[PDB]
Image (cartoon, rainbow, N blue to C red):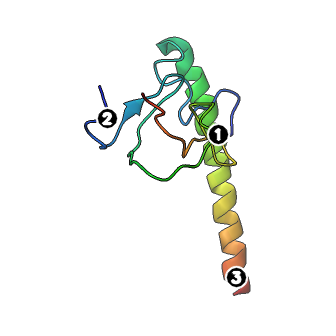
Amino acid sequence: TFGAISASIGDIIQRLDVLEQDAQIDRLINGRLTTLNAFVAQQLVRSESA
Amino acid sequence: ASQLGNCVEYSLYGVSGRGVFQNCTAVGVRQQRFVYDAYQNLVGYYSDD
C-alpha cells in the first residue's frame, strides 16, 4: 500500500472508471518506480563495499 | 462459484483477489471472515458456509 489508493493496482476497474483510474494508477506507477530506483542504487552501494 | 476448484482467482464477500485456496488448520477467531497477516493482505480463509 505505497500510494494513496493502492489495492495492489489502483482501483483496477472495480473501484474507479477509466479516465481517473489512469491518474491514480499513474501515481502508483511513479511511486513504485521510485522505490525500485532506490533499491538499485542501494544494491550498487553494497556491491562496491563487498 | 463454490469451492469446487482450489485453483487461482476468487471473490470474497468484502474483497476480490487472485489466490490458491486449501483446507488448512484452524487459525483465526472464526468471528470475522477475513484474517490478515501483519500487512495489507489476507492469508485469510474463504469462511464460506
Q: Residue at x 62, y 34 (%)?
A: A28
Q: Quadrant of residue A31?
A: top right
Which label was assigned to residue A40?
A: none
Q: Quadrant of residue A32?
A: top right
Q: Identify the subunit bearing mark 1.
A: B
Q: Identify the subunit bearing mark 3.
A: A
Q: Position of residue A40 (x, y in %)?
A: 63, 63
Mark 3 lies on a secondary structure that is helix
The residues tagged by marks 3 and 2 sit, at their Cα atoms, a distance apart of: 51 Å
* Residue farthest bottom in this picture: A50
Q: Between residue B21 and residue B17, name the one nearer to us.
A: B21
Residue on which the image places disc 1? B29
Q: How many neighbours does mark 3 have within 10 angstroms: few (below 14), some (14-19), or many (20 or more)?
A: few
Q: Between residue B40 and residue B2, name the one nearer to us.
A: B2
Q: Amino acid at mark 1?
A: Val
Q: Position of residue A44 (x, y in %)?
A: 66, 73
Residue on which the image places disc 3? A48
